[PDB]
Length: 49
DNA sequence: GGCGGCCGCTCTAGAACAGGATGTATATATCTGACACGTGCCTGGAGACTAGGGAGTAATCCCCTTGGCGGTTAAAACGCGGGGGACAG
Image (tube, rainbow, N blue to C red; front, side, top):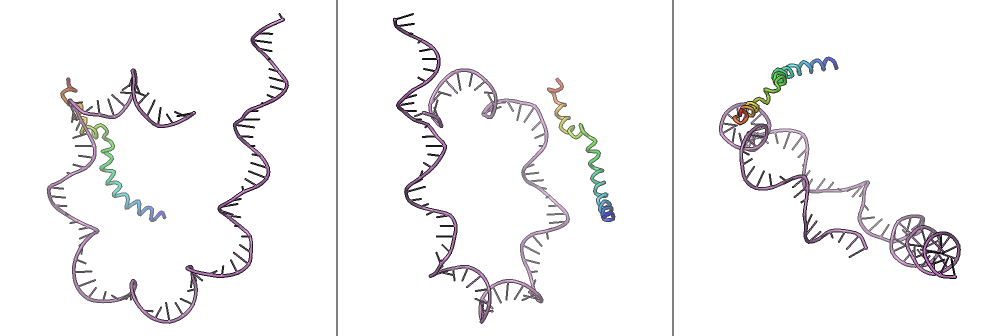
């Protein structure tokens, strides 16, 4: 059971690390994820007046 | 001495309780009539073979629905007045 468990963990590790590499920096960004709409919502005319 | 208040007597009666009534649920006796087992086939699918063609998969592409916003006038919702109708009788 440990042998097959370690083998399955090893074959999980590559795809798991590949997903983590692209999802961790997305998880770090909080305001930048909503900045695609915040930069248009807060930067208008009437907001500036 | 007369009259209002209080309590006992008596008529009325609401509704639970017991007995009669009639159509079914059961307790055998026996018929009975299809039910399933056996037999004899015999007719339809399975092993095996020939050939092929429409989808799984891969690729493209372009398309089209979701997210995501201001805007503004149409309207949902809250509330006041009230009005006619569902239901109790």
